Amino acid sequence: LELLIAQTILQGFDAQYGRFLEVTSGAQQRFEQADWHAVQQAMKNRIHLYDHHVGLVVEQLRCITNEFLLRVKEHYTRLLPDYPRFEIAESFFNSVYCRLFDHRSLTPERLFIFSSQPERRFRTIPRPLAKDFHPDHGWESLLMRVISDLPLRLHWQNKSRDIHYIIRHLTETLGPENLSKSHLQVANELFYRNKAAWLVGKLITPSGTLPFLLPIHQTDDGELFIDTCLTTTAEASIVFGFARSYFMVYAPLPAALVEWLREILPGKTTAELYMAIGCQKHAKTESYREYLVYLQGCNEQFIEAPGIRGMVMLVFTLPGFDRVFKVIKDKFAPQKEMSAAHVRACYQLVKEHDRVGRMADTQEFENFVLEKRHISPALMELLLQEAAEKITDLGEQIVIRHLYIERRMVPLNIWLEQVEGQQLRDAIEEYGNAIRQLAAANIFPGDMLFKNFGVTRHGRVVFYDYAEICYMTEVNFRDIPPPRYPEDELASEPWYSVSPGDVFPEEFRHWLCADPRIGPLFEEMHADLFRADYWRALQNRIREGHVEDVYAYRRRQRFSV
Amino acid sequence: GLELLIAQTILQGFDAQYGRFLEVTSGAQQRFEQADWHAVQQAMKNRIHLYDHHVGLVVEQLRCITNEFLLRVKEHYTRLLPDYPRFEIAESFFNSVYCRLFDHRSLTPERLFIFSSQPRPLAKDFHPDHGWESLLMRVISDLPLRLHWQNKSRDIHYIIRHLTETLGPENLSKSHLQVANELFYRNKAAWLVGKLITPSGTLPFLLPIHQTDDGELFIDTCLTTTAEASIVFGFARSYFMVYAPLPAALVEWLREILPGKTTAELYMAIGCQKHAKTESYREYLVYLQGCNEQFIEAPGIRGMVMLVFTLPGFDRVFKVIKDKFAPQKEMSAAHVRACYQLVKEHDRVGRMADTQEFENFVLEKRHISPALMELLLQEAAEKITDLGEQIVIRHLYIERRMVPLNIWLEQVEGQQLRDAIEEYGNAIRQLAAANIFPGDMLFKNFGVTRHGRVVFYDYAEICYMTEVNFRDIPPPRYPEDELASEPWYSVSPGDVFPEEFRHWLCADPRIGPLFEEMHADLFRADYWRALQNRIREGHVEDVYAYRRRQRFSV
Amino acid sequence: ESKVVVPAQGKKITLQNGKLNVPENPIIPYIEGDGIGVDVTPAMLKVVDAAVEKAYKGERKISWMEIYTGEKSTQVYGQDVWLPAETLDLIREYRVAIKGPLTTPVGGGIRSLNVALRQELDLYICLRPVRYYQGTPSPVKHPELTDMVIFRENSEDIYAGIEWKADSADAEKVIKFLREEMGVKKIRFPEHCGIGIKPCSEEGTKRLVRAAIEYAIANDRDSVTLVHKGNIMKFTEGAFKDWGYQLAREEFGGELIDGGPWLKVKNPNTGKEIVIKDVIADAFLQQILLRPAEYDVIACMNLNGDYISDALAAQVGGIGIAPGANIGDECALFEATHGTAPKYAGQDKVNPGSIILSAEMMLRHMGWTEAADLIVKGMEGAINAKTVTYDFERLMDGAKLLKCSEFGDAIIENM
Amino acid sequence: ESKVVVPAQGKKITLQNGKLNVPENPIIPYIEGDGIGVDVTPAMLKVVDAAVEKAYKGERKISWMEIYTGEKSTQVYGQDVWLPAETLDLIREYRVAIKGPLTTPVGGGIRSLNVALRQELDLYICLRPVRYYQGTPSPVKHPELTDMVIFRENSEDIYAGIEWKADSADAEKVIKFLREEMGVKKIRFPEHCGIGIKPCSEEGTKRLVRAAIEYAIANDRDSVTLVHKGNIMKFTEGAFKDWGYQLAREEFGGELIDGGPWLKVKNPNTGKEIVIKDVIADAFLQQILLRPAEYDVIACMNLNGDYISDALAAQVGGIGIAPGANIGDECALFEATHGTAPKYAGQDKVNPGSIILSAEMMLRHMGWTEAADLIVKGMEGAINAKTVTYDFERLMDGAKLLKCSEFGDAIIENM
Ligand SMILES: Nc1ncnc2c1ncn2[C@@H]1O[C@H](COP(=O)(O)OP(=O)(O)O)[C@@H](O)[C@H]1O
Ligand SMILES: Nc1ncnc2c1ncn2[C@@H]1O[C@H](COP(=O)(O)OP(=O)(O)O)[C@@H](O)[C@H]1O
Ligand SMILES: Nc1ncnc2c1ncn2[C@@H]1O[C@H](COP(=O)(O)O)[C@@H](O)[C@H]1O
Ligand SMILES: Nc1ncnc2c1ncn2[C@@H]1O[C@H](COP(=O)(O)O)[C@@H](O)[C@H]1O
């Protein structure tokens, strides 16, 4: 029987992933049909997809039955070698074990925290992913096999026009001499997100190997065109950013796709690369492992994340890691009036929402294990002081009941202290950009202070304390009343009744414009934000039901130029 | 079988009950003799609690032994009674047990003693063998008190005058006395009871002794009037503490003296309240068989706290607490009972009717006029249960029926009125000194006894006088104040201002002037403070059971 | 049976459709009242009828009926029938009536006549209107400005009186309920503490604000203000605002103004725009002194209401002559608002405005606006004439002291 | 590392055994504040600094050390460090402090710097003395008969924000609790209804009351008054009276007067006798206009406090120049009480009555009674003279308008 069980999980994974794929083959219609409510909508389902099957399995196991554990694994353990997507097969296994065991007691012997198999890198791939393309026999021709090449069932507008654009783009980028000697290896399958379907391929030059990315957009009224060509890693890293919804790309076997990618995305680690394609739950494992390597490889200890301490959350990081951990505090600051769940909800809501690459992705963790040896005194006292209910004492290890791991970014408030001159116009411009997108995305941030926004390597600005997070469809935007009387100017206390869930968008000025330096710019370019009229609109479109175009690139690059 | 064990057990139970009853009494002399007038009150307080204990005690015994029929016990128990000096209580004890066992259910002649089912000399006559002057000495000397006398030969002188005045002297030499071996002690007085026998008739003689401070006890007065006696044995006053080794005999003896009282009526005075309840019941039972009449809300002003009903020819009213109270009145239901209990324990100074609780009362629908019938349903559903032609009322009380004061006053021209007011006003005082403050002094809540005396009844608002603050309404600060409908000053719960009494008392033109005349003092904070003034200070005010005038100091 | 004649000539006020239909020849039920009520109440009859005779040309006359309650209650019906049932039934059927004052009960446990009457018939709105009568003596410099009508509700507020004494066992029970089961962390001191409960209905609230709007509508008022502390206790007090505004839109067709909460309600009778706005209470008390001009009709919760009504009146030196009335679903009663003041009674020396003034309301209430106004003219004019009773004359110089009965005449002549 | 520099010269005020020991070279921490705060604060320092020197012939000088909160802090400490924790330690370490204005968010999910400051220092008593000054424009005829000081508790009253919304389950859960287990029958319109909770604590009540009473004695006031709507709500408000008086008898040994509640407490230093008394809030509001002479000091529940304090000021025309402080077991902090008024930030237009006067509180509270006495002299002479800032001037007739900076001089001239 024991070996039976392994079959049960293993049967299970195959089942889920099959489901995963069918959801993901869905897109093209979804893109074409132009229904974008579905498209976001569908996205959400996947999240639920992995869990159901895991959920389904245990119940299956439970009915069965009513020491060997090493045995069952080995059987699961023993069925891997053939199986191409072995990797996920483990995770799924791991995922199951924990549910069975309430996320406790896991140990390498007990389950798969590390892979059984020898490293993936292939003798060869069963079906090659992408198709090399060659200039000769025309190049301008070349773009022809490519577009006429791809699947989508729709008409194209000013096709030549787009075509011309790229050739101009590459030419400037490379120059004809270099250009003649470089070629493309485009993906078999486009990657789909939101309003656009993306086309991924390498661009290979005498110099080296370069990303070439075109994202396909649907014109108003259903015509098709290509917004831009991005040939820089910097742009690429961004378009594969961690602040954006998972790409929906059809991969029969993920592991190969990743390998192909890295050259495109030299920066991103394996755990990350997995996310973009969309295996979040798998990422957890790798990401978990990847950290594990860090722990071996450093003598640093856990410390409070730099920034402004958090009224809602307890957060910390190893000095040299790229991610921070967030633990909801046992008792919130008095001024704050929310409840634990709500917080719990917010984070989830974010995972299931388009993030616009303004909202950092999150990974929940349960019953996390830490070695007392690791935890610095200053932090420990803090944990016990404020998170005592959550943490559990286990000899030299402690178990943190709830957790989140997220990208570690320099907090916004801090960045402004450091930066100056042009660089700053650089930042403020962005934050201002951030709120509009988020707002447009029917998410209204709450605090809005810099303490609650983060800075990327690329300088991009992202939103992270999800305290006071809400849809903009449940908030009423009001205009501060002109004072009735000359006396009115000076009242500490507003003389008009404010219903809760009331927002006055001229109030921010004080918090935002405090620094003399910061203030004019915001005024300079970002006037709209404080004008309650504007927000009113933003929510108006949304109520109208519109989804607004987001470009994971600079406006300039947009191929208008 | 078991039964004779059971029946004896009860019957035994009774005996004990009574003996203790006897011992507790015996003390009475010592207290009067001595000064434990607080103790006097208490013992009286406990005596009330004796009968219940043993009974309480027995059932437990029974249970423990405890764990058809029934009848066998009555016969067996019943068979015992002949050749028992005082069965009658013995029955009453029985019923109490049964009721206690069964939470007062299922009563029937069959099950228990609703109805009867079945030596030595109390007092020795005296004759004026010699001039009474000797005669009385025999009687005075004979008393068992162990204290000195003044006017020995003095008040002794006084007795004669009252004694002579009433009857022609030719009569005196003829008549003689039949005094009773036991003094009946009550309150601060030890009372001497005797028949007075003469050619015209045999008539009451009571002399109530008193203790001067560090006393040469003396006699306040002599009462030979037919009525006067009743007052002494009135419901309003507390039970006598008299030693009655065979009670029933005494009752018959007294009867001559108190021609008016129903037997049960007589039974309390000796202090056997629990039995009286039994007798209390039967007398009720004959009456309704006697005539066809329904039940009617007692004439008067309807009560927010209580519901009252009666029989037109009757002398008692049944008071049952409504479930839901008048909005203005805020008091817990339990609180009321407690009040009621209290009066039963507290000496009543002749101003408060005594009450007898009852449980699971039953009468059936024939006798209930619909109007009452609905009202009970409407205003007191929880407390009533419906069986057949019978309905059961869970909790109720019974008390003597008098005409509500409010009713009396519109039936009186002045002379009666003047008397009526005087009494009431006194009425307040006497309770007042008794530590009782009556919540609504309003007439609607005092009654006129047959003798025209005033007694307090709706006990809804009673409170000790040591729980209240007696106040002077403040003089107005400014002329604006004279015309304000709202108090400007901090008023506290239990703050009472007497002066505000006038408005209700003095409404009628006829009524008001006397009150100022007779009792200015009623409306003065000072007076109450003085009275409460002492009562903190130990003091117990002596309450006479006869007109003040009659006492010899006059 | 009852010892009150029902006047032959008169006719029963009647209500169908919830809008009063008042006959010309109406019958009105009045209670003379305890103490001074005898002094005052008669006058009002004199004035009221006068105002009625002149105003309508003698086409209409009022058939007074004297229902009885209080001490006089005793003299007639009973010796303790302080409040006979018939009366209530009289007020309920007749639908409008007026009374002198009744003895307030200072003592704690006593049963209060004034209250019972309002409470028993469930007159849940206590409407007091405050205005300044010229020549009157007042603290504020410019009290000419104040005309307001104040709507407060007797039922349903902290004025429930629901509380438990500290260490009541019962109360301690309540904390525990709250502190742990409810688990409120907001009680700094939970021991040796006593508690009260303040509540507000949707229903209770709209009970009156619906009313105010009708009063305002009927009488051509400019606006209605809802006073609340909805900045410290939003749900309990805040709610009041939230419903009142809501009520307006929902029943009375209130179009928005500038997104500011306030909305403008068209007046069906005249077509003018009634206006609804809200202002915080603690601040509002500041506003009345400073800007008495802007406020008109007011609807507020029981607590703010005592404070506010009680307050304006001082401002216009009208505590003496304030008029009041309470109103009910199907009954309304108009009351003299002052003490029995027994000592002076029968001397005919007291000041009769509040009671008379209450008449205006009554008269206004029944749509005899025209007459009701007449009293006003008479009553202000008489003062400005500075011919007045003992209360004023002492206060205001060069004034002529008038026995009370007389004053009514002065009121009338100035008319 | 703190950016705030301890003055070299000054010495720490220390508190022991309740009465604080203040040296003659105090260090008084200060906060400029946002907006108009730059304008006013510099002035007050001059005025206050001037007064001290003049009064004590220069023997006593105050070393002022600045500490920062809320706008400056972002500039000094961090971009987003609004309320550096250094500050809270600092005020507490040094016993008394003074605060310029701060920005209070309007609505929403945004925290308030003032409460936080009150809250986190647990400043439980808030004292708002009110006095008229000469020639301030007023709405009432004889304000100068108004010197009062008002004590409120921020800790415990109905202003504790314990309430539940209508139709919220808990609310209905709550209603059920009283209704069934508890047995409250008073509630009307229970469905669709919202609930609030009010508590009174012996510890809380005594705590405040002890506070004034000590005050009067400290400053030779003539009476202490307890304001409560005791009659309607016995248990929570009323218990206020019961508790407070009791405090006097037990703690301060007051001797009853005539058995009526009132009592006379001897003043140890003074030898004068302070009276302790109570009056109903409903009435009290009426009383303040008519008889403000009578009342010197007041103590009252939290609610009565806003309405009353806020309310008195209007009469005295003092909102503009209102003064305030919040007080605590270990510290007292005295603040300007007005909006920042950004528009006029730095312009020099605005008038700093409030902030100086708050200084005036501070000094008295420091026992430097004489110096504060000048400030009042200064403020008084300056206003009567009709030389003033815009806010007043616009009101008065024939004033001489002054910039903010100068007026503070003007006060000095009149010192
Ligand atoms: N990704 C991150 N990188 C660095 N610091 C972070 C990150 N996420 C959170 N923090 C810390 O946690 C805080 C955000 O959470 P939270 O306490 O709920 O909101 P608030 O910002 O009102 O106090 C930030 O102030 C920051 O200092
Ligand atoms: N002993 C009695 N005799 C006659 N009628 C009585 C007696 N006791 C009570 N009542 C009637 O019941 C009415 C009120 O009952 P009660 O309980 O005394 O007052 P309340 O219920 O107001 O406290 C009286 O007015 C009277 O009509
Ligand atoms: N507390 C934990 N510590 C380490 N890995 C975990 C923990 N919880 C879940 N995982 C891993 O998360 C991946 C998916 O598990 P689950 O979180 O159940 O979806 C697997 O690699 C698990 O081993
Ligand atoms: N509900 C009742 N119905 C009839 N008689 C009763 C009732 N309750 C008590 N008694 C009688 O009163 C006497 C004493 O009973 P108790 O006072 O209950 O001990 C007994 O003789 C009972 O028969």
Image (cartoon, coloured by chain):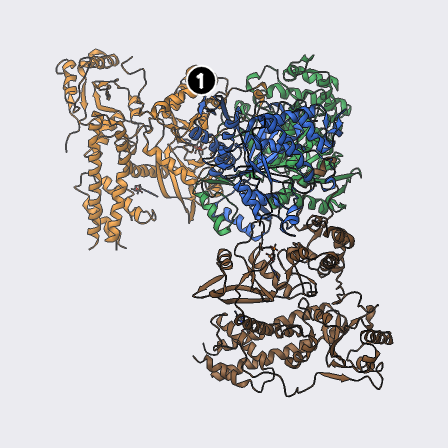
Chain colours: A brown, B orange, C green, D blue
Crowding around mark 1 (Cα neighbors within 10 Å: few <14, some 14 to 19, many 20+) is many
Q: Position of residue D310 (x, y in %)?
A: 63, 33
**Quadrant for ligand 2?**
top left
* Left or right: where B223 falls relative to C60: left
Q: Position of residue A457 (x, y in %)?
A: 68, 65
Look at the image and tell me whether residue D287 can be seen: no
Q: Where does the C terminus of chain A fall, quadrant-wise?
A: bottom right
Secondary-structure class at tag 1:
helix
Can residue B340 be seen here? The reply is yes
Residue type, mark 1 in image? Phe
The residue nearer to you, when weighing B268 against A441, is A441
* Vertical placement of residue B196 versus A287, above or below: above
Q: Quadrant of residue C313?
A: top right
Q: Which chain does the residue under circle 1 lie in?
A: B
Residue B445 at x, y = what percent? 43, 29
Q: Number of numbered discs present?
A: 1
**Residue C94 or residue D401, whichever sits in front:** D401
Position of C215 compared to A83: left or right? right
The relative height of residue B511 versus residue C88 in the rendered view (above or below) is above
Residue bearing mark 1:
B515
